[PDB]
Image 1 (cartoon, rainbow over the protein chains, first blue to last red):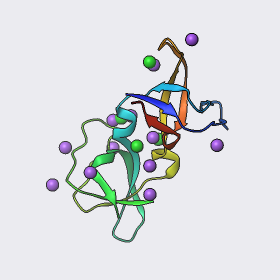
Image 2: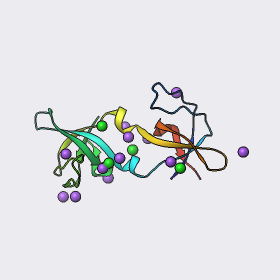
Image 3: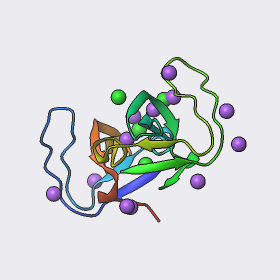
Image 4: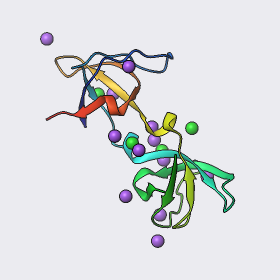
Length: 60
Length: 61
Ligand SMILES: [Cl-]
Ligand SMILES: [Cl-]
Ligand SMILES: [Cl-]
Ligand SMILES: [Cl-]
Ligand code: NA
Ligand code: NA
Ligand code: NA
Ligand code: NA
Ligand code: NA
Ligand code: NA
Ligand code: NA
Ligand code: NA
Ligand code: NA
Ligand code: NA
Ligand code: NA
Ligand code: NA
């Protein structure tokens, strides 16, 4: 979908993208739909990593 | 922050992570607060790409 910038942003890394308030962007739906996550075991320890659907997750 | 899975999920690709309803996850702000975006010019043309904090963005209306 299409988005507008609300505030100026200064990138810190080369991969980040600086912009100004009012700039317009295209963002693919997949960026909101997929999250890299760490699965925790019953003791709260990391046991797996991978992409999971954002919307299969709820705040704990 | 921590999250809970609402339904079982079967990964389709190697990079996806299978899980069960009720599993608990850590998801970093450095992951989910950022989207890869394409900056556009006034004619709708793509002019730059990179990670942006998505909460600095509002859907256009
Ligand atoms: Cl998101
Ligand atoms: Cl993906
Ligand atoms: Cl990653
Ligand atoms: Cl585009
Ligand atoms: Na800023
Ligand atoms: Na993705
Ligand atoms: Na949901
Ligand atoms: Na929050
Ligand atoms: Na289920
Ligand atoms: Na599934
Ligand atoms: Na994926
Ligand atoms: Na996997
Ligand atoms: Na992200
Ligand atoms: Na693009
Ligand atoms: Na113009
Ligand atoms: Na938000």
